[PDB]
Structure formats: structure tokens, C-alpha cells
Length: 107
Length: 7
Image (cartoon, rainbow over all chains, first blue to last red; front, side):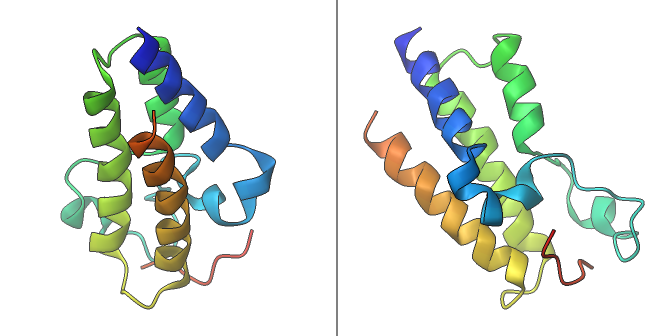
């Protein structure tokens, strides 16, 4: 229970104004109808995003912090898999993942 | 894939 409270706090920080300039691509599910994304679901078998993670915390779907962390890392991994490594969204992902990993390590 | 983002 205490683990999951910390997970909620980590996600709240990831949604916070101070990180918004690089966190915003991850707020909502990737829009697969947008121009250029017609192949997203062919490449990414398990989409994930911060609003879906929030809804799962609110439904108590995660039984512990490790399950929550797996979905956060899935979100970042999907970004690293789909996009070219030099893409601006990958640099944003690395920054937000640093925010996450330092908090998740220290809970 | 994804375009230049910035918003």
C-alpha cells in the first residue's frame, strides 16, 4: 500500500508543470490516426501512456510497485522502439525516464 | 512516423 502511494506520487510529478516541456508526448495514448502513425500498431504490440497508468493505479490494478514500474518502462521502450534514435521525442523520453528512474530507485 | 513535435 505504501509502495503504491509512492508510485502515485511519482506519476504526479511526471505530470507536473516543471517537466511538461518534455513529458507532454507521454500524457495520452499515441494518436494512431495522426499523419505518419499508420504503422504504429504494427510495430508496437502493447501501447502504454501516463493517463492509462494513472487509470490503472486508480483502479488498483497494480498489486505492487514492480508492476507499475513495468508499465512505465513499457511506455518508454515503445518510444525507443518506434522512433529513430535521433528523434526529438526520444531525447524527451530519456529526460522523463531519468526523472522516473531516480525517484523509483529511492522510494 | 512522428513529426517534429513542440506542442
